[PDB]
Image (cartoon, coloured by chain):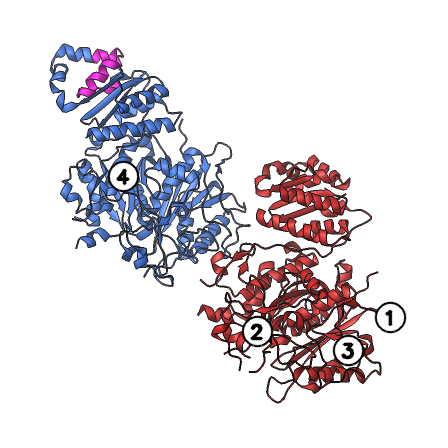
Chain colours: A blue, B red
Amino acid sequence: DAIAIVGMSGRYPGARNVREYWDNLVHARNAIRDIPTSRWDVDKYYDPVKVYCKSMGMLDDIEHFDPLFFNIPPSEAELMDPQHRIFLQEGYKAFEDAGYNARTLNEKKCGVYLGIMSNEYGVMLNGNSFAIAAARIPYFLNLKGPAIPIDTACSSSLVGTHLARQALINKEIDMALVGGVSLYLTPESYMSMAGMLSPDGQCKAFDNGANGFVPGEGAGALVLKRLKDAEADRDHIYGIIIGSGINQDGKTNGITAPSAKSQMDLERDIYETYGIHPESISYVEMHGTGTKQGDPIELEALSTVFQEKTDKKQFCAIGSVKSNIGHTSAAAGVAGVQKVLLCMNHKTLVPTLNFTTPNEHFEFEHSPLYVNTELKPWETADGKPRRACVSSFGYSGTNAHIVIEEYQPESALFVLSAKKEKQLKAYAEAMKDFVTSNEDIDLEDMAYTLQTGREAMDYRMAFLADSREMLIKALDDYLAEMPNGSIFAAHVKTKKSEIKLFETDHDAKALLQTWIEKKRLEKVAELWVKGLQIDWNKLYGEYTPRRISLPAYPFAEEYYWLP
Amino acid sequence: DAIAIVGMSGRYPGARNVREYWDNLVHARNAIRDIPTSRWDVDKYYDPVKVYCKSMGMLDDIEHFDPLFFNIPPSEAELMDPQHRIFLQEGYKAFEDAGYNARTLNEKKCGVYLGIMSNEYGVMLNGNSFAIAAARIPYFLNLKGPAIPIDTACSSSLVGTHLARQALINKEIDMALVGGVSLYLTPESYMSMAGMLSPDGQCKAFDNGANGFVPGEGAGALVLKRLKDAEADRDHIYGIIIGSGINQDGKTNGITAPSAKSQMDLERDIYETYGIHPESISYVEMHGTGTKQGDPIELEALSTVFQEKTDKKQFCAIGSVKSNIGHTSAAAGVAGVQKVLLCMNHKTLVPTLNFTTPNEHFEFEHSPLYVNTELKPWETADGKPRRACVSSFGYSGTNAHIVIEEYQPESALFVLSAKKEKQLKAYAEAMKDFVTSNEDIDLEDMAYTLQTGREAMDYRMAFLADSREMLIKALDDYLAEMPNGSIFAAHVKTKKSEIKLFETDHDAKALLQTWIEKKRLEKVAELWVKGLQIDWNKLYGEYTPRRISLPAYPFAEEYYWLP
């Protein structure tokens, strides 16, 4: 039936994670920049009539990777497509976002569906096949669900989402990691213009001045489960997918042209099959690439299908995050789904950018659709959950469309760990920022997530806090190396002898069990950082706190590029 | 029958509007200047025996346009012939001069007849067809009458006037925008000398030293209606067209030579068809280009036709504004008509320039005609309305001649608005200058015109005044941002919540309606600036004021040229 999204991770232009992404969206920030010479020299390719676009939505530090984390020899990292490397990281973090770790994922029937559409790095070099790109994560985590890369161009990650959905519903897999990744590494590939790109370097979605898209880079991942499992497993749930479908344009006027009829059929068939009334939908994240003939066709299609079922006018807001971050290609779908989920979570609609005058080829006034350019509350009538759609169409003519519905649910011991001390320090910094930024965090939930929802790695710290302020201070004290009697830290490999007593002796174990039983945290803390395995479940009696979203592993930022 | 001229707008050398035009004419100012290097370098083309003229009647700021006002993307502005852009502005302003706005013009059967004769910008670039030049305004305002460009060279705008008149009389349209526009952008075009140009750079109309014309630039528009409609609609009326005709030179000695016989026939046929006696005419705005063989032929023709009917001598003044502003080509006719209307309105004849000694080939003394070189009152006998003619002849041999007759008619709340705040400030400045210059302005008429005869746009200010002095001070206060409790100003998009109450509630509406009916102007003002729609008609009971000519929109002065 319904598919729960229980984890997410994202890395987009101007946004190192989905929290920065959200902030950028709320503040209507445009992340498109001029392409610097450190990528390539636009002056050597630029002609205004060769490339006619000099702008891109760029990721930062596309060369950074933590190969040791993934048991990859540093020398192999130079030979890896950075698309592979970045997704490997973002995929992993999506799992951690959900609160799953290497231990809990081992041998899971989790499918991996990865949107990817370019080979630039592999060619530059003359390991890097699409088949291997998808398989990295399964290999690393010992997952057992199929690993399939999807190249349907810009619809790729949304196509992957559909396929994962059908596999989960058919009970062929019990979890799915779906994602996309797109980089533009060469003048040659970003180049193909074929007339596709805007000379101004903006996706002017819905606007009469729409004249092409600006290429964007990105990597995103979602963790999907059957809703029934997600609730039984007490996952945190971002939203549910209640309908999806894919189809083809077929014969168009040129293989890259869109078909109004196919878009309508796709949308109609989904709504009919899954019993979804257009009136119930209040936002659609359009494909919205800002092409002159594409935009009006998408608008007319969607408008027409909505109007078949309702006379209501201007109830459904439309937007496109491509106005913010550009056209992130294989990652477009996942970028859009993540926007919608963040909107739902915050019950907030955010501005779509670059919209001055409506596309002349479409009349909004008597449409069910309106372009939202405001930061405003996302209103819902009565009890009803918010519903939104995401569309993604590819240049090869393979379309996708999904429907998402908002999910309506019915002292603590903080522990951190990393594979190196430097990353542990980075982790503490990330947690401090997170806690500083989120004044309403549930402290018991957060600890519980750190305990059960992260792998205990070799470098460890832990501390007690009963308040946000105490929590922030502890992390400050840790970072400043300023003495605090409630902070404990150790490298596990150093402390083996100091722990053995609690691992082998029967009454020491009984004492440890009573400590965890008779509620003492300082003692549990000291032992934990030294490497003692704690049974975290015993810490909780009648009341068990829930996993929540926290910052994921802060990978080492080591530079690797062509050998 | 009679055609009323109910709106005008003009932009000529030395005159940004028809008010500056009038001032220049009254003061016998010559607007011809040496061609600056910012246009082209005359030294690179100049040969005295190549160009042999270095002078031009030039428009200022031919590159300026406000594309956002017209819902045109800024980048499209660079690709538009400035002839199109300038006429789009003047044409619009003519409508506003008449007191008509987008709302009142929507779906109107208004024909647009546009004099235009050159393509320089389009060629320079290698949207810019004559057909599109004419269609710009209809497309913007949603007019439904035919949109036709006319290229009969120099007679163009007068030919258009004839066609509009006939369509109006035949009830095919209910309004007409007629105009012309000419620019001289290249050395090549302005160049064609073909022997046409004066080496001295003056149009020496009627003078024995006449030796060619000096090219001038210009853009001018008129608003025409049937007189019966204009009186029923309570338009303000500049004058009435009581006759017009067009014909051809046919076979001449060279296709650009004039025909005495054709000019006589044209004039004779018009006077006979429409029952106009030459004795009733007291001024003729001649084609008067200051060419050696052209001038005497025109004089002899007109003199002969007049003399066929009367023995009276030297009763009809002749002149040519080309002596002031040069030969404005496609806009020549509208320039001439506008001069005559202004003369009529002020009951004043103005000097024609560059006249020292009469052309030897014509004897004035026993003619009905005399050259007026004086600023003097336009005298009329008995009750009789003043009558004048305008001639315009083209190099292709298509001639035009119209007859115009003087029209003899049987605290306030000031509101201003623009699409940007900067233009609002420019609007207030223009109004202050206008009121300062026009000491006799009817304050009630003016307010009424601002209320009913201008579109309420997004940036608003309003105030009360019961005198000219109070009005001027209010505007000064607004401009100087110095506190004045009777001044209100808002951006409408910002205030939506503060207005909704008066839009939905039944008793609030009844209060607002009572306010409007009891003339509670402060209250009406505060609400209007915030975006509340006011039914202005309710402000007026037994006495309704009349629309008058006021300054029109002050377009943003943004520079656009070749991409």
Mark number displayed over residue B370: 3
Label 4 to label 3, Cα distance in Å? 91 Å
Chain letter belonging to callout 1: B
User: What is the total number of numbered labels drawn onto the structure image?
Assistant: 4
Horizontal side, residue B489 vs residue B380: left or right = left
Please, what is the three-letter code of the amino acid marked with disc 3? Tyr
B444, A547: nearer the viewer? B444
Are callouts 1 and 2 both on one chain? yes
Mark 2 or mark 3, earlier in chain:
2
Element type at mark 1:
loop
Label 1 to label 2, Cα distance in Å? 41 Å
Return the x and y of residue A148 as percentages of the image width and height.
Answer: 23, 46
Q: Are marks 1 and 2 in contact (CB under 8 Å)?
A: no
Quadrant hosting residue B245: bottom right
Please, what is the three-letter code of the amino acid marked with disc 4? Glu
**Residue A111 to residue B254: above or below:** above
Residue B277 shows in the view: no
Are callouts 1 and 4 both on one chain? no
For the residues carrying marks 2 and 3, which lies nearer the camera in this image?
3
Main secondary structure type of the part rendered in magenta: helix
Question: Can you identify the residue that label 1 sits on?
Answer: B381
Horizontal side, residue A77 vs residue B204: left or right = left
Question: Can you identify the residue that label 2 sits on?
Answer: B117
Chain letter belonging to callout 2: B
Residue A397 shows in the view: yes
Span shown in magenta: A513-537
